Amino acid sequence: QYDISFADVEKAHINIRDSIHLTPVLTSSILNQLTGRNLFFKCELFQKTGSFKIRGALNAVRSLKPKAVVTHSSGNHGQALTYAAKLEGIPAYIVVPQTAPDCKKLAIQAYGASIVYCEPSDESRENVAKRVTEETEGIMVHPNQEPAVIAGQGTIALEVLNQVPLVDALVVPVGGGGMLAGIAITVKALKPSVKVYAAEPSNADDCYQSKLKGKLMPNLYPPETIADGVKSSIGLNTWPIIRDLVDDIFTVTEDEIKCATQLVWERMKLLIEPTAGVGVAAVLSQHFQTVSPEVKNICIVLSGGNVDLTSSITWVKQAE
Amino acid sequence: QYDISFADVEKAHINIRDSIHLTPVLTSSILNQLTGRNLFFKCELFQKTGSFKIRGALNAVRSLVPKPKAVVTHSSGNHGQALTYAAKLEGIPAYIVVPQTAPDCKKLAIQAYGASIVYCEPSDESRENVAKRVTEETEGIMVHPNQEPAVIAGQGTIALEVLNQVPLVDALVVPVGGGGMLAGIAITVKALKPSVKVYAAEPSNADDCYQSKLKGKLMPNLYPPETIADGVKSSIGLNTWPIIRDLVDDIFTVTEDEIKCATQLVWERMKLLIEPTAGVGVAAVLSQHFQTVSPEVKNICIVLSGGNVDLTSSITWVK
Ligand SMILES: Nc1ncnc2c1ncn2[C@@H]1O[C@H](COP(=O)(O)OP(=O)(O)OP(=O)(O)O)[C@@H](O)[C@H]1O
Ligand SMILES: Nc1ncnc2c1ncn2[C@@H]1O[C@H](COP(=O)(O)OP(=O)(O)OP(=O)(O)O)[C@@H](O)[C@H]1O
Ligand SMILES: [Mg+2]
Ligand SMILES: [Mg+2]
Ligand SMILES: [Mg+2]
Ligand SMILES: [Mg+2]
Image 1 (cartoon, each protein chain N blue to C red):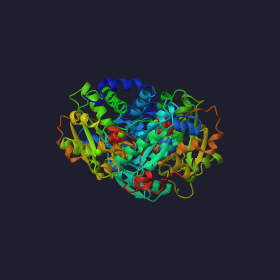
Image 2: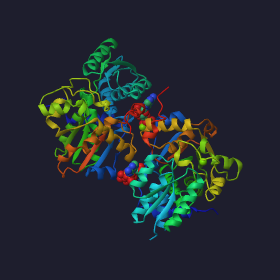
Image 3: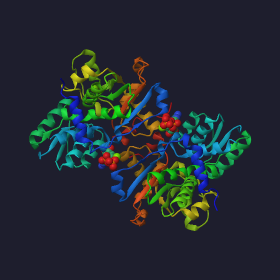
């Protein structure tokens, strides 16, 4: 028994299928050549609010009249929860790290939420959200540890398994592990021979360290990574699922993330945020070569497209 | 009559369909809200080589194989890449004449697809003259980016798709450079559904098409244009001008700032990495002058013509 069940994911699908489009799966002959795999890209960047977080947000809201919804977010969960709350006429307060990209801070306010900045650490996020929840008498909807959220994210895999029936592996970027855990439950329940692989920045590598050690090891210092959506540590609800049901974790460096993100931009014309480049970098990575040649058909989740163009100017690289 | 007919477009479709993408039409609630219209975006940025030019290039190569020592053209980059790809499929060397001031991303892709690149001065005259000389030197066949009939016919296949995907469209909005796409679309639309408006969108900083229509004669750009819309610096030509004169309903000019704003809006709201030239059509629908367009012209298809953007080049203006 885990904090969600397959049944939870099925119910989540029922709860949100009238509210979100089924995002496309796209392909690139070039990326296929570069990796020597048969790649399929699940385009969550086209989801309402620009990331898959709409799934968990809609599921959580439908599963909840309350005075307000509250959460902490690097931006995507915040935008998504604000939109879902607004559908129901519920006020939203989003606790956001000071260092979040401007595009995410501005979008949250565009959708009508009150934004409250916190310090960029797990502790500050959690503590400030708890206080805001107390002060507003709101309902806290955690970005990755809330069962209704995790089950919502898992619906990605229901779609993938139908869109790509012969898939051999899903590759999933991991932060708090909400998406990874929901996908792992879904894939392992329906099609256990399909691999579930996590992709994680080296600069925020708690999930990798945790799996290696076989115990939950949160990030010690606040992470600094261009993959701004996966700075969260994994938590007590998602760790057991990841521990038991995820096949392997691949870490990728800042430079690998930057190169893979630009590659998708230039070759596929999909404006993924760098956090979504993490999964692409994983498949391009040296260690991924160790993956059996039999694992041919790989679906990478392009998890979001909320990228700060003015910020991306710092690191955009000319061909060398 | 004109240098192509609808039968030419139909034939082009037969010639190329097995080799190209039927590109999607995407939408955005936000862009609808901002413009007050119901917009349909024809996503040629997902075409092979990153723009619609694969259509004209494949058509020309398939039409003109009946093999030369080489194919030659001049291009700001998109036609160059497309022709190189089409030629490579047939084992034919490519020579592309490219203005010095073309984006690096385009210069490098042409080289990556295996062509020889020859830089020219950034003018209509230099492009045409150097391409002529290279054709003669290589004993190649010249495939013009916008005045070659097989190229015009190929580009018009966009409209065949649009009219099936968006059957009750009220207007198409099309960025114009040399007028190959505009003319091919105009021919197809006015043949199949003449009540559908065909509108061109053009940078004010390269506004020969607008000036031509305004003055009722071909008025090429007098100075080399300077515009972020790097793929529409070409003047319209002798084969496309009569089609545009007679069959295009209106031309909307847009400033550099409007192009930048519309390009970023598509990036941020729709996550489609259009090049700024493809932003020209979006900026037109957002422009003050487009507000003079009747409210009954509500359902509008904009051609997102390419996605070949130089991100290093974009740093200067991205804000
Ligand atoms: N004010 C804003 N500032 C920055 N980004 C914004 C702003 N408003 C919306 N966005 C971004 O625009 C993208 C699209 O938003 P959203 O999904 O709400 O609209 P849409 O794409 O028009 O909707 P649909 O595709 O369902 O018609 C998201 O990535 C969102 O973050
Ligand atoms: N070396 C390169 N430098 C920059 N851009 C490149 C380079 N090679 C290819 N591109 C760009 O990559 C994009 C995709 O290229 P292309 O259509 O040939 O392949 P693909 O997208 O992998 O193919 P498909 O979608 O049919 O599987 C195009 O915009 C092209 O300009
Ligand atoms: Mg492609
Ligand atoms: Mg981590
Ligand atoms: Mg959208
Ligand atoms: Mg012009």
